[PDB]
Image 1 (cartoon, one colour):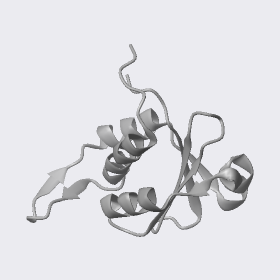
Image 2 (cartoon, helix red, strand yellow):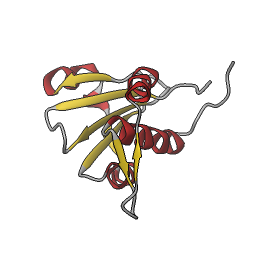
Image 3 (cartoon, rainbow, N blue to C red):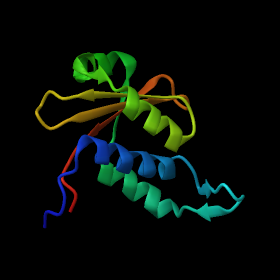
Image 4 (cartoon, one colour):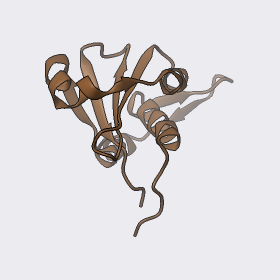
Length: 118
């Protein structure tokens, strides 16, 4: 049952929040509060996002090369993940594909297709 076809901007917001949870077992709040992130959630986020992991070489052949740097999306992502990030978007394939690299894994590209939300 379809629910949402998100804009690229909305998708980036969604992706950032979920990747932030992928990244840790505890969300650290401004006030020093730590919200636990159940492992099960992290496993399901990874699957539901349809993340593929690419080496630099493989990425450059699988769609990264046509992907263009998005400055606002990159900063928006960097701010949520809390570290230097690059977001590129392959607007080929008509349905966008987001390519993400972070300071945490400088030799891995994260490939995430924009999809329907259900």
